[PDB]
Amino acid sequence: DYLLPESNGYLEPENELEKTFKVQQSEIKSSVDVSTANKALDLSLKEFGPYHIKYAKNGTHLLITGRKGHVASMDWRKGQLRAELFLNETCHSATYLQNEQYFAVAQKKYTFIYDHEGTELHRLKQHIEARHLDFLPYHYLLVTAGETGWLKYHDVSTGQLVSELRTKAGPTMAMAQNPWNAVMHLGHSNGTVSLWSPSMPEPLVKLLSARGPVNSIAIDRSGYYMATTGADRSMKIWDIRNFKQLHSVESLPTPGTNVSISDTGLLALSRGPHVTLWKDALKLSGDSKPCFGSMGGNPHRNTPYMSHLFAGNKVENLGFVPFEDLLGVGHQTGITNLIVPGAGEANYDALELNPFETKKQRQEQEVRTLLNKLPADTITLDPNS
RNA sequence: AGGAUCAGGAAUCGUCACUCUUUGACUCUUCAAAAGAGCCACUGAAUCCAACUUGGUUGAUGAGUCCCAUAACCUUUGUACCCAGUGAGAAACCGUAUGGCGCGAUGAUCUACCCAUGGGUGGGUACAAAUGGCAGUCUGACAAGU
Picture 1 (cartoon, rainbow, N blue to C red):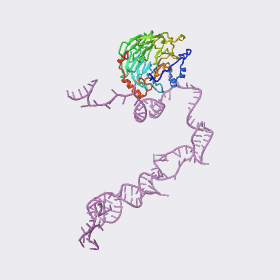
Picture 2: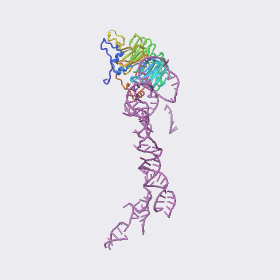
Picture 3: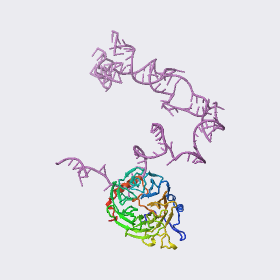
Picture 4: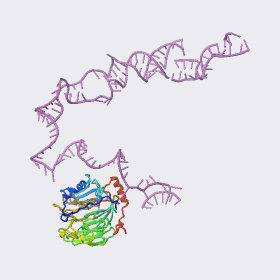
């Protein structure tokens, strides 16, 4: 416990009169240290479509996918850029599967698996739609939910299809994989998120999450609380460990396009022109219920921790850097990294992921993970069963 | 009982550098062109002539010192060799009872042609040497900067 060398950043009001959420990002960029203040990027690439964002599980490479033709893998911290592909088919998402050397893009029809340089490795005959393209490196399993009812699991270690699960739910409106559990979460128009394992052809458990369609879903690091948003201007705080929505934030001004969860407990809600993050909102009490406005400054009622409004955009998606305190918000013209104080964890474990990794360390670690892949039957509702 | 498909056999390392090779990108680029998201304007840079400046036939520029003119390769004139080696063969007595260089392995013996073992011609090989060949003592008018 005392070996833990680095401690989180904080944000403190210092008055009741002074307010926490009112800080702006140019105002933040004054006091943050120079490399960390400079780690906020403004990539306005206004020519192509709205931009999809994903950092790798280590923050070392950023992958972006504009809706029209852009596919871009930068070695994000440095000036290096690996991939810049212009496919005139339209794309939806992308993820690095194992390392920055191999990634996968979610196109109009077919998923593509791709080299760092931008070369074509593997076009999938299957995956005939691809809306959410997500990965779990602990099974080496690219799990993809298109606009189809089905859900496809490709084991890119072997390079073969594991399984394909028809939901009977229709087009997938959301998918968030569980880091702690590797159960997949699919969200559809009935207000229903289904938990999934590749073995079980019926879902593990269905959840009538909200009314209307599922806008998005996002899961804790601990796998305890998953924050779900419907298109009904509502966001539920599901505690998966006992399958209860802790708080039901009703009547947003606009339904959130996405939700995202940091490591230390931050929650990101992006209505699209606005991005708003709460601190410690996932806890058990309804005092920790995330609320927009606490009248009278009552400590029980909970205000948002950090706010932002995008002027000329309706942003697409967002994702924290997993070890740093920023979050990449993909807007129509591009990418902002909005600086949080305490979102990411300060003390990573190198033996799990390496944010500072040599290429020789990388090819050691890749072989280490491929030795430690699990075959797909081990995806279960509990890791420990 | 012997062989080939799905126990007679070394290989369990959380990488640091260094070098080498390899392919790929890359600014370019020849094969060798051809096509040009086209037009204005603003502004910048570069080049070329004119111009001007400074320096210059009291010499500006151009220039394969070293690959050695300090030579190479010969050519003629004076010497050392060999078709150093050969190695057992060369010449017929003795001061005042007694004493020896009287050879010689530890070396006796020699150093392709004609002429009765006297002399040399011819070729290869090496050097000294050349005021010998091969092998005939630079340019000279712009340059450079804006």
